[PDB]
Amino acid sequence: MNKNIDTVREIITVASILIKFSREDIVENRANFIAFLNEIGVTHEGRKLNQNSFRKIVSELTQEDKKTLIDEFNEGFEGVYRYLEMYTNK
Amino acid sequence: MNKNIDTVREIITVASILIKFSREDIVENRANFIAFLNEIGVTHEGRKLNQNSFRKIVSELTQEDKKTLIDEFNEGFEGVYRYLEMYTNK
Image 1 (cartoon, each protein chain N blue to C red):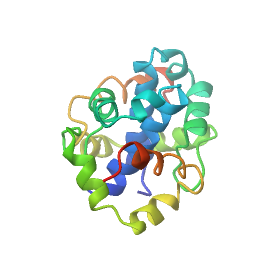
Image 2 (tube, one colour; image 1 turned 90 degrees about the horizontal axis):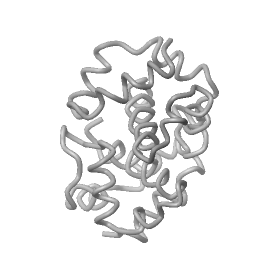
Image 3 (tube, chains in turn purple, cyan; image 1 turned 90 degrees about the vertical axis):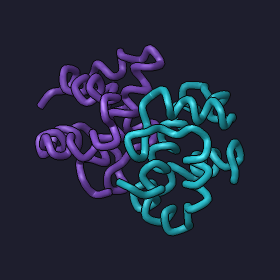
Image 4 (cartoon, each protein chain N blue to C red; image 1 turned 180 degrees about the vertical axis):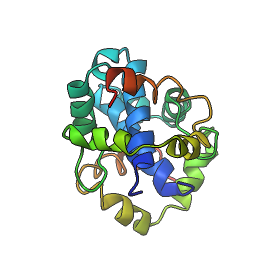
């Protein structure tokens, strides 16, 4: 669980929960998204994300990570993994 | 990502988001918790959880899974991994 895929699958799912709870306002901003991750308790090494984490995650996130996480996240992430980008694309 | 630790770390985090959004009502019931997992889009093999998944997860969940997921989830899961139990303990 020391890969982007983990903090990613998690980042997407959670921020999507937000979007599901009519919290697209939190999912639509980097600060809210980052804080969201820092409040519910999502980390990638005993520490949540400050602002760079996700950036490096996605920066080092490949279409294979998408493939492997899609293996389980078939079509239930095409509007969350993509949404995080439109709201926070790096 | 084909272990309990994944569907667990996810189950906890998400249901905790619920609890964070004053949704302890959803986190406090197996049906709501299961549905919650089935609505936001959390799966462990291209399929969410119907009711048995979590049960077998936790049934096959060991203190080591807790250790490894605690490695990242230091003290931010002592009221979520334990909460899922009080609400759904098998």
